Image (cartoon, coloured by chain):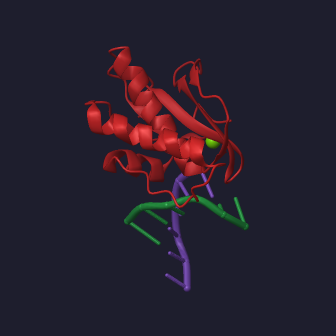
Chain colours: A red, B purple, C green
Amino acid sequence: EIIWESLSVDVGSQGNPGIVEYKGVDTKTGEVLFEREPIPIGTNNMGEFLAIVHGLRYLKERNSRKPIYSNSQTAIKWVKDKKAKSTLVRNEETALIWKLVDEAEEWLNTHTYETPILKWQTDKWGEIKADY
RNA sequence: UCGACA
DNA sequence: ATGTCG
Ligand SMILES: [Mg+2]
Ligand SMILES: [Mg+2]
């Protein structure tokens, strides 16, 4: 019951909070479709959110109806709400991620999409295909 | 008091 | 260890 015709996203970090990156891959083949340049300070959940929204934009611009898989219960909710409820402090070190998060929410408030955003069931299926 | 997803 | 939700 894995929908193989899908995009899978995941975050990678060093520290949490710490250096965050994310990527999107074809669930079937593992082909890397997008990979964000490391952001110097962010949280896991912020990254997971940015990964989903990147995915939405990526599929929309390509006229693709594929669903997105994420393993992140938090990020799935934040995208549904159009609001990333992060605790991360705001300062000059966290300005970049917070700018990206604000711009992701703005995108969600200005665009439509029909893309199903699905939970990857790790306990049944193993690590998501985009894992680091 | 946890439980869960990372 | 921390970041987050039910
Ligand atoms: Mg993940
Ligand atoms: Mg992972």
Q: Is residue A59 above or below residue A101?
A: above
The image quadrant where one finds the C terminus of chain A is: top right
- Give percent across and percent down for residue A21: 64, 36
Q: Is residue A43 left or right of residue A68?
A: right
Name the foreground residue: A24 vs A28.
A24
Residue A24 location (% of width, % of height): 54, 27
Residue drawn at 65 percent across, 28 percent down: A37
Number of residue marks = 0
The image position of residue A40, as x and y in percent, is 69, 41
Residue A63 position, x and y percent, is: 32, 15
Identity of the residue drawn at 52% across and 46% down: A98
Horizontal side, residue A3 vs residue A65: left or right:
right
User: Relative to residue A87, is residue A39 drawn left or right?
Assistant: right
Q: Residue furthest front?
A: A92
Name the residue at 29% across, 39% down: A109
Asked whether residue A108 is in view, the answer is yes
In the orientation shown, which residue stands out farthest toward the top? Answer: A62
Q: Nearer the viewer, residue A78 or A109?
A: A109
User: Which residue appears at 54% of the width and 40% of the height?
Assistant: A125
Taking depth in this image into account, of A62 and A102 the one nearest to the observer is A102
Q: Is residue A118 visible?
A: no
Q: Quadrant of the N terminus of chain A?
A: top left
